[PDB]
Amino acid sequence: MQAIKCVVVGDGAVGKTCLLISYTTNAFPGEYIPTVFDNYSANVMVDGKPVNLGLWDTAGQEDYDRLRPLSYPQTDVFLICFSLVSPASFENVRAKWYPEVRHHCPNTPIILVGTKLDLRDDKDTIEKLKEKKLTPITYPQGLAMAKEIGAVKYLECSALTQRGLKTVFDEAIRAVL
Amino acid sequence: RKKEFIMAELLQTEKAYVRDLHECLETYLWEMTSGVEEIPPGILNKEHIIFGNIQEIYDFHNNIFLKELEKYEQLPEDVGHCFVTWADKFQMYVTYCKNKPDSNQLILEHAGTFFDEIQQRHGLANSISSYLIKPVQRVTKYQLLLKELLTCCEEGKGELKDGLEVMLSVPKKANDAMH
Ligand SMILES: CCN(CC)CCn1ccc2cc(NC(=O)Nc3cc(C)on3)ccc21
């Protein structure tokens, strides 16, 4: 039965850990956001076919450019994430994440994931960004970025509401089959 | 409350890390050193290259560090000192990371399904590769937990900043040591 290594990369601001915890436990962790998500595997059925999905977190490694690639080899699919309410994390897709992922795993599929979808319509978030002469990242921006990096899908999700979250991972699997 | 949750995570994740290294050592490592099973010649007597100094890292955590962290359970604002105390021992993460690429190449090029067979046999969710990234993960994680403590511990927080300093400096040193 088919094994799938999925590595999740992106800035600290994406909430990689929270994402994975919320997907795996079926619930936003709420009270306390743990900093530790240990390498995970579970069976899921996709398009009928059952599959063994491996998830690796990378949080903590954001400042260690030579340590991060230690997780890259033999990856079946990357989730490259940015927070939809951080223009900087978006720009880093282009500036930092796509380059090193391509440099090490040139023929590995990428899903581009916009996180914190629930904050894109939040007045306080919106206002905190307008004060910095910025706005949240909207859909066509994600699409355009995905095109530019050769991402197979651009997907948006919330660890909070679970909106789009199961789909992110369905599609990570579909991109390998 | 937040300081208590973080400490609890530090402790629970430390326990699991010790469990995970132990598991690695007594499955993937033990099969090779045992001499119970058929060992691909491309890796024979190269367990040094595969597992680097993971034994010594496990021994640190299992003999000392976990016991000392436990002592700081009700002292989250002071746990930074634990890292200061035991800083030199963390230098062995530099050696480990330096070696990890060589470990990975070796396993691709010469190990075939040796370790997969062992994984299947023992019923392990984690592959040998999943176990072997863990030291790299763990050594970048401690700084996260210390930063989290800092967001919620008062001006009694130089007993964290030095701890954090240490745990920022170990992974940077490991980073800067890579080819
Ligand atoms: C203004 C600061 N807020 C704290 C964030 C305060 C209000 N608030 C509290 C928790 C919380 C949580 C979300 N939303 C998420 O974390 N979405 C995620 C994460 C990932 C990954 O993907 N989606 C929104 C608002 C919230």
Image (cartoon, rainbow, N blue to C red):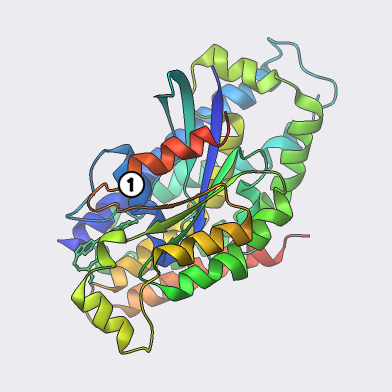
Q: Please tell me how crowded label 1 is: few (under 14), some (14-19), or many (20+) other residues with Cα within 10 Å.
A: some
Position of residue A41 in the picture relative to residue B130 (left or right)? left
Q: Nearer the viewer, residue A64 or B52?
A: A64
The residue that mark 1 highlights is: A164
Q: Nearer the viewer, residue B24 or A69?
A: A69
Residue A18 % position (x, y): 33, 53
Question: In the rendered image, which quarter contains the C terminus of chain B?
Answer: bottom right
Position of residue A26 in the picture relative to residue B100 (left or right)? left
Residue at 61%, 41% in the rendered image: B54
Residue at 62%, 58% in the rendered image: A149
Q: Secondary structure at mark 1?
A: loop
- Chain hosting mark 1: A
- Residue B138 at least partly seen: yes
Residue at 48%, 68% in the rendered image: A90
Whether residue A125 is situated above or below residue B74 in the rendered picture:
below
Q: Quadrant of residue B109?
A: top right
- Residue A66 at least partly seen: no
Q: Please state which amino acid type lies under the numbered disc 1.
A: Gly
Q: Quadrant of residue A3?
A: top right
Residue at the extreme front of the image, as rendered: A140
Residue at the extreme right of the image, as rendered: B41
